[PDB]
Image 1: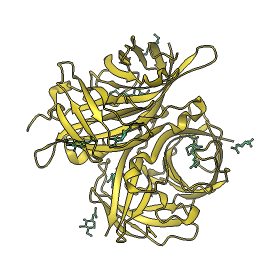
Image 2: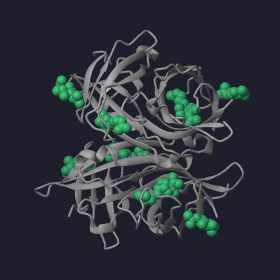
Image 3: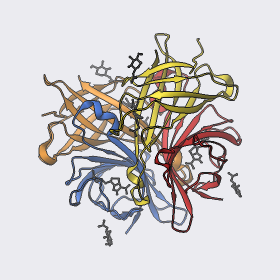
Image 4: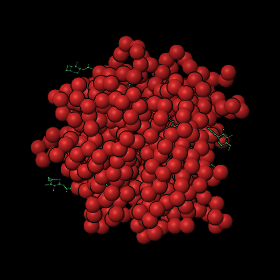
Length: 121
Length: 123
Length: 123
Length: 121
Ligand SMILES: CC(=O)N1C(=O)N[C@@H]2[C@H](CCCCC(=O)O)SC[C@@H]21
Ligand SMILES: CC(=O)N1C(=O)N[C@@H]2[C@H](CCCCC(=O)O)SC[C@@H]21
Ligand SMILES: CC(=O)N1C(=O)N[C@@H]2[C@H](CCCCC(=O)O)SC[C@@H]21
Ligand SMILES: CC(=O)N1C(=O)N[C@@H]2[C@H](CCCCC(=O)O)SC[C@@H]21
Ligand SMILES: *[C@@H]1O[C@H](CO)[C@@H](O)[C@H](O)[C@H]1NC(C)=O
Ligand SMILES: *[C@@H]1O[C@H](CO)[C@@H](O)[C@H](O)[C@H]1NC(C)=O
Ligand SMILES: *[C@@H]1O[C@H](CO)[C@@H](O)[C@H](O)[C@H]1NC(C)=O
Ligand SMILES: *[C@@H]1O[C@H](CO)[C@@H](O)[C@H](O)[C@H]1NC(C)=O
């Protein structure tokens, strides 16, 4: 019963939309971030992911990848959709932001990590 | 320099294998993952993964991310990294991952996420 | 702008409390942490912590890190973050942590590290 | 019997020393990194940490903080000391590098994560 489909916003002011989830748990979406680590102008970017359907849990885990359209980086988020007594949903996620580096010797510094909480609308 | 491509069969440094299919013009790909190690005693099942490669500036060593939707637990893992040509000329994926466990209630969310690394090379 | 200082009693967003003592001229400090939550079935006990604040350029919002040496589990947590003055003028510590569980075999080292955030405010 | 005391090197060519561990599990050390995220010249920097002494485990966990002397950042490492059949030790660790940001709205991008394996030098 906690569904990922909808329009969500996070603590930083970014918004995301997620469409219908198919029977395979696959979904697509859009992400408009309010903040960036680049100096490039932000552009709405696509996202793709899946919800885990094992045991058809009411509060499933999920993951998705945001394919940034204004930088060479990629972010992944994973988390769980929690739904209260009243039907109010929260997604509690963690993410990794992968920057592009030119030299393999600099790989060690390429991955930032953090949390995000999404609520609806 | 060679272009590093994600399509192919890979193995990681713990002996898990994944196969990634063709990457489409939107940077999307599908594959399967067969893990050698596990955080559950349930029998391991090949599981699908889906992700994208970043094609901005058409870099020869692109970043990417994907989600593995495990078929034998309620967890999900995400990986992100970059496809490099290594110093010896081989393709290698340098990745980090978050493994999200399912918790029964929200007050246990703090303990639900593991993190680590993996390096993949082509099989 | 106030200088954000780590000395004091703090509480987090899960009800855990910590107390940090004076910071010496080398940036070192000691404290105690009383966690509201645990991943063990042991009785929680107050545990020591030790860490440092970075004093380079004597920033008024310095970074810092510390290790909590749990006295009721075989695990270790490390925290690192920055002491900020918030938009409302209050001190706030914004931190990230890694909780390292003990495993028995080196093959299981990949599942030993959980990650998360904590924000602390002064009590 | 796996002991943190010694000189170690990691997989990127950084070295560290750790001195005697006291009965409270406390130790001090030094760290000379081979790599940096700053453009400042590298300087050997002190570290302080603890090993967990509960049940006096033969392969203890531990954590420590490196207080960089050439940047405003801090890195913390945590991991476990493993020791094999003939006494060969390896420290398997993960780390968080906290950079300094000027404004609290940029906190989200301040923390990088990675692994490090140390062996005896
Ligand atoms: C709220 C939150 O944590 N995030 C959010 O909504 N936007 C930022 C990042 C934006 C990356 C854009 C591409 C780039 O700068 O390379 S993904 C994690 C973080
Ligand atoms: C090599 C490596 O680090 N990993 C790998 O290849 N398999 C494991 C995890 C498998 C999770 C299976 C689902 C579950 O147990 O819930 S994903 C990160 C780790
Ligand atoms: C609030 C927050 O995120 N944390 C907090 O205040 N307590 C928990 C963990 C406590 C570990 C106790 C020892 C053990 O169970 O192994 S450290 C991160 C987390
Ligand atoms: C091997 C490994 O991963 N690390 C290592 O030995 N040095 C780098 C970083 C050095 C930070 C220096 C201070 C700064 O640049 O601000 S700590 C993690 C990483
Ligand atoms: C989020 O949606 C709200 C209004 O619905 C808008 O005010 C805000 O600018 C959006 N955020 C971004 C980053 O577009
Ligand atoms: C990885 O593929 C190799 C070579 O085919 C195979 O022998 C091995 O069993 C595979 N690993 C897993 C976990 O299936
Ligand atoms: C935090 O300190 C407050 C105020 O003294 C107290 O009510 C609460 O029990 C403490 N939390 C824990 C985990 O001890
Ligand atoms: C590490 O110690 C080795 C052996 O002395 C030395 O070759 C190397 O330069 C040291 N690394 C650094 C970053 O000092």
